[PDB]
Image (cartoon, coloured by chain):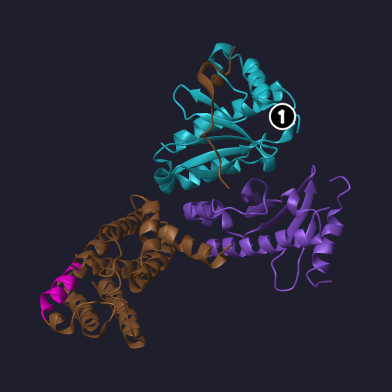
Chain colours: A brown, B cyan, C purple
Amino acid sequence: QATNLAANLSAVRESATATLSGEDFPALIKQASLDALFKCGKDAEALKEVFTNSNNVAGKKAIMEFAGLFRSALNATSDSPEAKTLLMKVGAEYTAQIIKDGLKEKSAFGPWLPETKKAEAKLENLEKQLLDIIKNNELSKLSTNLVMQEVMPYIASCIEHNFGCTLDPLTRSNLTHLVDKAAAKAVEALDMCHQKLEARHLEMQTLIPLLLRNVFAQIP
Amino acid sequence: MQHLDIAELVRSALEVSGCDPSLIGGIDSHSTIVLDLFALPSICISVKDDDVWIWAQLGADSMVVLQQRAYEILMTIMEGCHFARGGQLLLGEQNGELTLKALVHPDFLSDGEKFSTALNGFYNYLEVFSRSLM
Amino acid sequence: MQHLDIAELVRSALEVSGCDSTIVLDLFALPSICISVKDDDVWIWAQLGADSMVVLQQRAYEILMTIMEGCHFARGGQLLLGEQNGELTLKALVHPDFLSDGEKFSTALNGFYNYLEVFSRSLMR
C-alpha cells in the first residue's frame, strides 16, 4: 500500500515564487538577552521591531535592564509553579506596555531609571528593604506603610532629578498624586506576589526588581 | 551530482511511494517542485548550487507558537534525521513563518527508492513539527 | 577529500595564525574543542558544560533564536546542537569551501571559537 505522503498528496506542481534564503557577535549576545524577555509577549518579532526602530536611548536601556533582571528571575523561579507564573505574568505585562507605548521620544520607559550612582544605590537599598518588610510580615497596615515609605522617595527623586523624563520642571511640581498612586500600585503588586508565593526568599529577591520596574512602566 | 535530474528523481520517488501519477503536473522548469498535501503545509524540493533541499513553511502563527514550544522543538531536532547532511533537520524562517529544512545527503539521491525514503521521512517530521507548533 | 589530511589542515591553520582519531585542540586562553573526520565530513565541536542540558530547557527559545541567525562556515548555513557525556554540544559540519587550505580553515576555527563564546554566555547560570 501507498505511503502516507502518497495517500495525502493533493498535487505536484512547480513554482517560480517558492524559494529559500541566504558577523556582529556583541549584537548577537544582546539579542539573546532581549529574546528571553520578548518570548513573554504576544509577538516577539513585533517587539524586536519596536525596540530596533527606537531612538530612545533611556527607554531601550530600561528594557535591556529588565531583560537582564528577567533572566536572573527565571534562574530562581523555575522550580516553583507560583513563582514562574508570577514571572511570566510580569513579562507579559511589561512587553504589552512596550507595544502600547511604541518607544518614541515621549515614553513610559526611561524616566524612572537611576541617573546617578547615588540613585542607583538608593534603588538597590530600597529593594533590599522591601524584601525585609515582606519577610517580616496579606500585607498589614504597618508593612504597607513601610513599603510606601521606601518607594515614594525613589519616585520623587526621579521627578526631581531626571532628564530621561522629558517634562518641564515647573510642570513636574503638579505630580504629587503621581507619587502616591504609583507607590500604592507598588504595594498592590508586592502584596499579591507575597500572597501567591530560603528558596522563597530568593524567589522574592529576583521578583521585586521586575515588579517595581513594571509598576514604573505603567505610570501614566 | 551534476547530471542530476531532480524532476525525474521526484517522479520516481513518488512512484515508489505509490502516488497517483495523474496528480503530477508540469515539473521540468528547474524551479522549485511543490507537493501540496491534504492537511499539511506543502513540501518544496529544490536544487541550490548542487545542494538538494526539501523544506516546508510551518504556518502563519508558527513563530509566535515557537515562543512557548521551543524546547519540544529542540528535542525533536536533536533526535536526528538519517537522510540529512549533518544528521539533523534545520530551522529557518520564510515569509514570517518558521521553516523546516533538510539538506539532503547525497546517499539519498542515488535512486528513487532512496529519495522516497527521504521524502516520506520528511513527511513524517513535517507532521510532527507542524503539530508541535499548533 | 580522501586526499584530505585533517592533521595537516589543522597544523596549517595554526601556522598561518602565527601559532606552533578526533583531534582535541586545547590552546592557551581558548576552550578545548574537537575536530574530527567522519565519513568524509569534517566536524568542529565542543561540550558546553556540566549543566548545559538543564539550561537548554530553561532557555530553549533564546538558544534556538541564536542558532537561527546562522553560521557562514557551516554546511546548511547553521550550527547544530548535540549531546555528549550528558552535556550539550555545539557542532559545525564544516563547509568544503573552508577545507581548501590553512587560511580558510583558520577562519572556520576562529569563527567556531567566536560562536562558542556566544553560546557559552547563553548557557551560564
In the image, residue B121 lies at what x, y percent?
61, 29
Q: Amino acid at mark 1?
A: Leu
Q: Residue furthest bottom?
A: A118
Does residue C16 appear to the left or right of B34 in the view shown? right
Q: Label 1 is found on which chain of the structure?
A: B
In the image, residue B92 lies at what x, y percent?
53, 45
In the image, residue A53 lies at what x, y percent?
38, 62
- In the image, residue B73 above or below residue C32: above
Residue B106 quadrant = top right
Q: Residues within 10 Å of mark 1 (few under 14, many from 20)?
A: many
Does residue C118 appear to the left or right of B98 in the view shown? right
Residue A92 quadrant = bottom left
Specify whether residue B36 is in view: yes
Magenta residue check for A179: yes
Residue at 56%, 64% in the rendered image = A24
Does residue C72 appear to the left or right of A87 in the view shown? right
Residue at 61%, 33% in the rendered image = B46
Residue at 66%, 37% in the rendered image = B84
- In the image, residue C124 above or below residue A120: above
Of residues C30 and B1, the one drawn nearer to the viewer in this rendering: B1
Does residue A95 appear to the left or right of C115 in the view shown? left
Residue to which mark 1 is pinned: B109
Q: Secondary structure at mark 1?
A: loop
Q: Which residues are magenta?
A: A174-185
